[PDB]
Image (cartoon, rainbow, N blue to C red):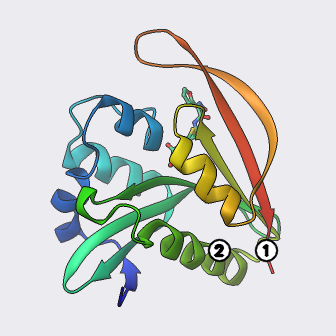
């Protein structure tokens, strides 16, 4: 793919907010959100986070991610990882994760990137593993139906 990236803009909101296809996908990428997803919920996330970035191919916004934790000189934690349904498995997430790693190193002087992935998200767990992330801990969380899920906390040194 001929991918580029830039900071997320207002005009991208409607597109990105269309990416989660069901409650599970929304929970996996934004567990505080309530289905149905909306532009206002995405904009609120952006306002309270850092680094919101889109990946673009052939004029189309295909990916989005941000940081929900950032500690200068230490680490960032990547979240809100969303990819357009027509572009899944084509390398958009891996591209964007690489972009966000550079942004963490360069702008936050981070030595580590943290990613948390829910247990049900096999594709996520396998991709982050391919990208050199290692599992560090498992935490209990609850899904929207009040059922227990396992949040797998992974990390990777930067550089
Ligand atoms: C306050 O912490 N509560 C969390 C909690 O760990 N949220 C954290 C938070 O924000 N994350 C995000 C996020 O919103 O970007 C994700 C999404 O990750 C990816 N890979 O896209 C995983 S979870 C973590 C939680 C989860 C369920 C109930 O509570």
User: In the displayed structure, would residue 42 be above or below residue 24?
Assistant: below
Say left or right for 29 vs 142: left
Per the rendering, the mark at residue 76 is: none
Say left or right for 35 vs 53: left
Say left or right for 94 vs 114: left
x, y percent for residue 111 = 82, 70
Q: Residue at x 74, y 58 (%)?
A: 133
Compute the Cα span from label 1 to label 2.
7 Å
User: Closer to the camera, 144 or 43?
Assistant: 144
Q: Is residue 77 visible?
A: no
User: Closer to the camera, 124 or 41?
Assistant: 124
Q: Based on the displayed image, in which of its 4 quarters is residue 107 positioned?
A: bottom right
Q: Is residue 58 visible?
A: yes
x, y percent for residue 54 = 36, 72
Look at the numbered discs 1 and 2 and tell me whether their residues touch, using CB distance below 8 Å: yes
Q: Secondary structure at mark 1?
A: loop
Q: Residue at x 16, y 58 (%)?
A: 14
Q: Which image quarter is the C terminus in?
A: bottom right
Q: Secondary structure at mark 2?
A: helix
Q: Which residue is mark 1?
A: 158
Q: Residue at x 40, y 49 (%)?
A: 45
Q: Based on the displayed image, in which of its 4 quarters is residue 132 positioned?
A: bottom right
x, y percent for residue 36 = 20, 32
User: In the displayed structure, would residue 35 be above or below residue 6?
Assistant: above
- Lower sequence index among marks 1 and 2: 2
Ligand 1 falls in quadrant: top right
User: In the displayed structure, would residue 122 be above or below residue 112?
Assistant: above
Q: Which residue is mark 2?
A: 101
Residues packed near mark 2 inside 10 Å, few (<14), some (14 to 19) or many (20 plus): many
């Amino acid at each position: 793919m001929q991918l580029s990236h830039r900071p997320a803009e207002t005009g991208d909101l409607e597109t990105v907010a269309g990416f989660p296809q069901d409650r599970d996908e929304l929970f996996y990428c934004y567990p505080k959100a309530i289905w149905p997803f909306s532009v206002a919920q995405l904009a609120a996330a952006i306002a309270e986070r850092r680094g919101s970035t889109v990946a673009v191919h052939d004029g189309q916004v295909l990916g989005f991610a941000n940081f929900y934790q950032w500690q200068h000189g230490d680490f960032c934690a990547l979240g809100n990882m969303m990819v357009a349904p027509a572009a899944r498995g084509l390398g958009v997430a891996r591209y964007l994760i690489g972009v966000m790693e550079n942004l963490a190193r360069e702008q936050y002087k981070a030595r580590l990137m943290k990613i948390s992935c829910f247990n049900a998200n096999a594709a996520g767990l396998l991709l982050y593993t391919q990208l050199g992330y290692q599992p560090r801990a498992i935490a209990e969380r609850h899904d929207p139906d009040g059922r227990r899920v396992a949040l797998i906390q992974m990390d990777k040194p930067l550089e």
